[PDB]
Amino acid sequence: LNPESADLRALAKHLYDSYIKSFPLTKAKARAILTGKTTDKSPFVIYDMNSLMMGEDKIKEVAIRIFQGCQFRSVEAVQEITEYAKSIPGFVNLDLNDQVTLLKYGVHEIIYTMLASLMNKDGVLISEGQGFMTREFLKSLRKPFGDFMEPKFEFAVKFNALELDDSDLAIFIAVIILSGDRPGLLNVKPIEDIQDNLLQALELQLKLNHPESSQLFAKLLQKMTDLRQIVTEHVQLLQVIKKTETDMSLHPLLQEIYKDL
Image (cartoon, rainbow, N blue to C red; front, side, top):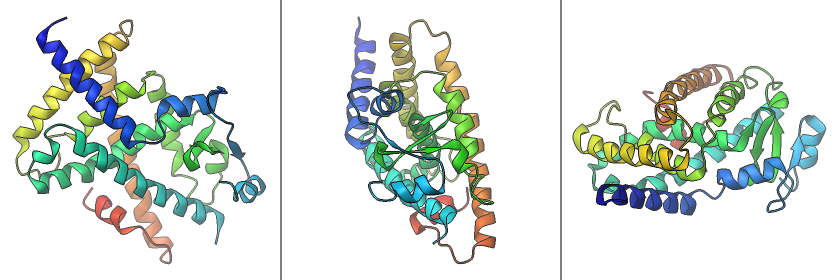
C-alpha cells in the first residue's frame, strides 16, 4: 500500500477498462461459451462440409471462403487494436510515423495472442462466439489453406496454459505495442519509457493476480519468441498464396501491414 504501486494499479485499471471497451469478445466470455456456462449460449459447431454449409445462415470454394472470412475478421481486429492503442497513455503523443510503425508490427502479435483466448485444443470460436470451427476441419482444408491454423493452435495450447485473464492481457498487449525494437523507429527513447512503465505495471499485476505462479512474468515475456515465429510463418504462407492463387485478393490494409515484415 504505497504511492508507486498505487500509480501502477491505476494504470492497470485504466488499461483493463479500455480493453473491455475496445474488444467485444473477451476471454471471460469466450471461456464461458467454451466450457458450458449459463451466462453464455452454445455455439453451433462446424466440423465438416455439411455442418459448414448448414451453419452458413445464423453464423466460391470452401477453403477460400474461410480464408476470406478470416481476412475480414483480421481487419476488424486491427481496427480494434488501433482503438485500444490510442488509450495507452503517451501513445498518441508520439511521432505519427512511429505510432504507425508500432501498429504495423504490433497488430499481428496481438491478434494471435488474443485469438488464443478463443481457442481450445479442439477448435476456435468464430462469428463473435456464435460458432466453433474444429481444429481438424481447418487442418483438412486443401493446401495450402490447411496449414494456416495449426501453428496458432499449438501456440494457444501452450499460451493458454499460463491461465491469464483479461486484466493481465490488457497490459501484456500494451507492452507488445510499445516495442522500441521495431524496424524504422524514428525516436525509440520515449517508447521505451512508456514500455518500462507498462512492464512495471504487468509485473505488479501478475504478482497480485497470480501470487502462487512463480516467474509468470518471465514466462509470459518468453512467449514473444513464439509470437514472432508464427508471424513470420504466416507471411511466408501468404507469399505462397500470392504466387498460386493469382485470382484471390488480400485486403490492402493487410497488404501494408504485411509488407517488409
